[PDB]
Structure formats: C-alpha cells, structure tokens
Image (cartoon, rainbow over all chains, first blue to last red; front, side, top):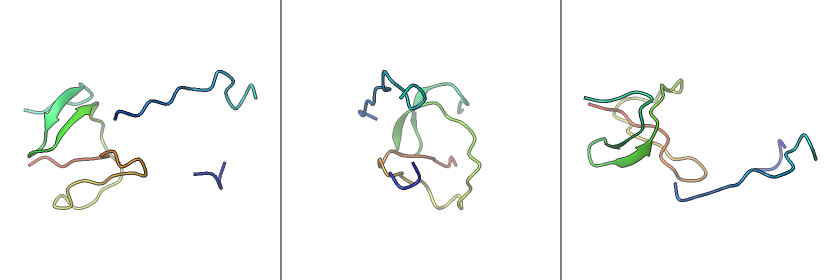
Length: 20
Length: 48
C-alpha cells in the first residue's frame, strides 16, 4: 500500500481489501 | 454570498467548479490561489 501510488469514475471492488 | 457544505456550481473569479465546499486544514497564502492533485482536479480555492 505504501509503495503503490471530475469525469472520472472508480467503482469500488466487489471484493474490498478486507474480504480479499 | 457563498455556501458551506452545500454543493453548487461555484465561480470563484472565473473558476467554475462543482462539488461540496469543506474547510481545509492545509493553508497556503491567499494569493496562492489553487492547487491540483495527482488526478489534476482542483483541491481548494480562496474567495475575495
């Protein structure tokens, strides 16, 4: 998590980080 | 007059933006007008 980095739509994962 | 936490199509001296206005705990100088994040969306604005 530390190392990874209007009109835009992001849909939440059906499997969030917790369930994954 | 301006509004707080009430979404509007605000025009801060030629800057047209839509969304909710919430108080910011990061403070630049008022003359330093606005910034943009990694997504290049406007993050703050100062009113006269």
